[PDB]
Amino acid sequence: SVLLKVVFLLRSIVDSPYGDLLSNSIIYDVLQTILSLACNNRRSEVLRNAAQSTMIAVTVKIFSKLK
Amino acid sequence: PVTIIIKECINLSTAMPFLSGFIQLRLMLNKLKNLDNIDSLTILQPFLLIVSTSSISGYITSLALDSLQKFFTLNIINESSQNYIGAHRATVNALTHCRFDDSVLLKVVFLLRSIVDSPYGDLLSNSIIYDVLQTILSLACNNRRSEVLRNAAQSTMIAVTVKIFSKLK
């Protein structure tokens, strides 16, 4: 549940208007961490599903910035 | 483009009265040049028929909900679409009724979060948001489910409470 709170706050911070101000060397670290959470099968499956949905929800924001 | 919906239709067709509806949907959306005048309740009604009923295994429901989330995230339905208000009304309306192990419910909860937080959630009728709040509160209060799903329920209800009381201005 702590990691779910981590992932939820990551999504909340990145999606809000106070996410463009993040330095571009940091969002790579966020993506790497959510990937390391998602691929690892030792965690709970439902947490993995949450991480996957979070990572889609930030990937859409990242690639929409390419405009 | 709007070719995503036919792709999701063929993706969900591999389930081996609803398959006939989906194949009719594919034959209808052979048409090109955007969704156009289509009467957009029917562009995605068979997806709601999958989740609304209570006689289908969880795998197909998860696939249908993934398709719905894909449609919303890519924003297939927009202001230009005919009768978009009715479609976005119906999609929240169907999820409140019966469904379905726990990942399906989390998918429903995440889609509810994404729909309500967005601009289109403002267009929902005030008789419906009460049903959504009742459903999420039933998820949160109940303890038979897994704890992490309960925490997700907790967070979404906080978020939609902030979104609702912000409208009181």
Image (cartoon, coloured by chain):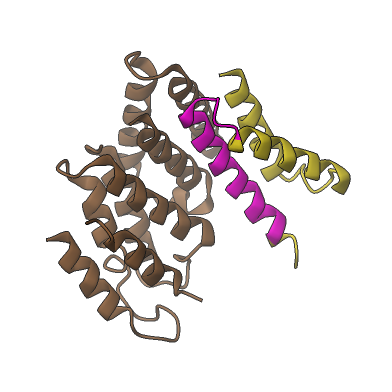
Q: Residue furthest top?
A: B143
Q: Write down which chain is painted brown.
A: B
Q: Nearer the viewer, residue A45 or B129?
A: A45
Q: Left of A46 or right of it: where is A60?
A: right
Q: Nearer the viewer, residue B88 or B30?
A: B30
- Identify the main secondary structure in magenta: helix
Q: Is residue A23 visible?
A: no
Q: Left of B28 or right of it: where is B33?
A: right
Q: Residue furthest left?
A: B17
Q: Left of B42 or right of it: where is B6?
A: right
Q: Write down which chain is painted yellow.
A: A
Q: Quadrant of the C terminus of chain B?
A: top right
* B96 part of magenta stretch: no
* A48 part of magenta stretch: yes
Q: Where does the image place residue A53, in percent across and percent down from the top left? A: 54, 43
Q: Residue at x 52, y 56 (%)?
A: B73
Q: Residue at x 59, y 49 (%)?
A: A56
Q: Relative to B33, is B96 above or below?
A: above
Q: Where does the image place residue B57, in percent across and percent down from the top left? A: 22, 42
Q: Left of B169 or right of it: where is B24?
A: left
Q: Where does the image place residue B9, in percent across and percent down from the top left? A: 33, 66
- Quadrant housing residue B83: bottom left
Q: Where does the image place residue B125, in percent across and percent down from the top left? A: 34, 47
Q: Residue at x 67, y 53 (%)?
A: A61
Q: Relative to B143, is B61 above or below?
A: below
Count of numbered badges drawn on the protein: 0
Report the magenta residues as a range. A40-63
